[PDB]
Amino acid sequence: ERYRAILETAARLICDRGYEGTSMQEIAAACRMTKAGLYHHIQNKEQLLFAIMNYGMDLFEEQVLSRVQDIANPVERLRACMRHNILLVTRGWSKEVIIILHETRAFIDARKKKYVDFLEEAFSQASQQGLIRPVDPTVGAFSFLGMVLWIYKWFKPDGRLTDEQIADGMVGMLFPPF
Amino acid sequence: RYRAILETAARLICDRGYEGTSMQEIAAACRMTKAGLYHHIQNKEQLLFAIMNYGMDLFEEQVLSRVQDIANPVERLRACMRHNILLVTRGWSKEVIIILHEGETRAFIDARKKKYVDFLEEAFSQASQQGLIRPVDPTVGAFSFLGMVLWIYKWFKPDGRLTDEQIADGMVGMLFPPF
Image (cartoon, rainbow over all chains, first blue to last red; front, side, top):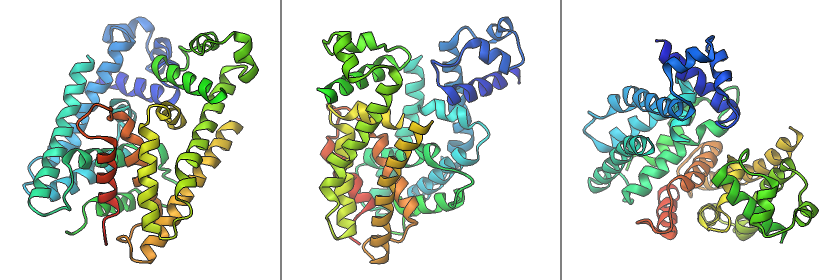
């Protein structure tokens, strides 16, 4: 419990002022610990970032992939996955962890590729079964990911559009009745 | 010569970071004296705003000026998307644009960015009302377009399986098919 709290706090600080502009002393004080206490849990800044990103992938698999991987119809699977990814970004409890994850290298890269593989497989199946307009599966996957992963840069919760309207509109754009 | 400086600086900033990169290092990468650099840019704040303003100039020069006269709004969106993907992927412009999206100066750039979004929203509005695209909230349309296109820098390489043109043909076909 104390460790995940450290990752969440560090992630919030890193998102506010960026990686270079965040010190381990800043992170320690934000966690109500001494710098020595922080280093009991983490080895240095580079490992902290790795830990944040791995925790991010865990959270994503639990809250997005776990829920959709058993949907057999590939366009239903895509539609649910896109809606879950959007709502993760706008409603999630660890938004800054997720931002760092998509914004040791080889270990995280291979984990991220599992999601790209999943999307490409579904676009492939949906295209083949006549449930979506044909498209190259990679073009589909990365259009999907670009639409969802950009949200945090523009979306203002106090603005006109609601996050449910964004989810409905986005899904309807890529995956209309076809 | 000024634009070459900004492109060289954008390269270093993307490779070493903004805090890592110094005006002395920029001068050396430009093969200029510190005095010659200083004539164009005097500190790092000035440099950053200059690069971001150059990026918005590129949206005008490489995208808007090429499409703004297309009367049919779906044809306009299809051309705008293709030009924008090229601006994101061309070696000479790609790092300027990355920096653009990665106090009072913040509002001056924000206002320029919003003129582009406004343009996309007007085209989505016209195309939807005219039945040339499936109905969509114009802001949703605009930022779906923007996310798709700007995120290309995260995964594109010029020796990848898909060319830039294949990516554009495919993206335009997804958002703006015959309808």
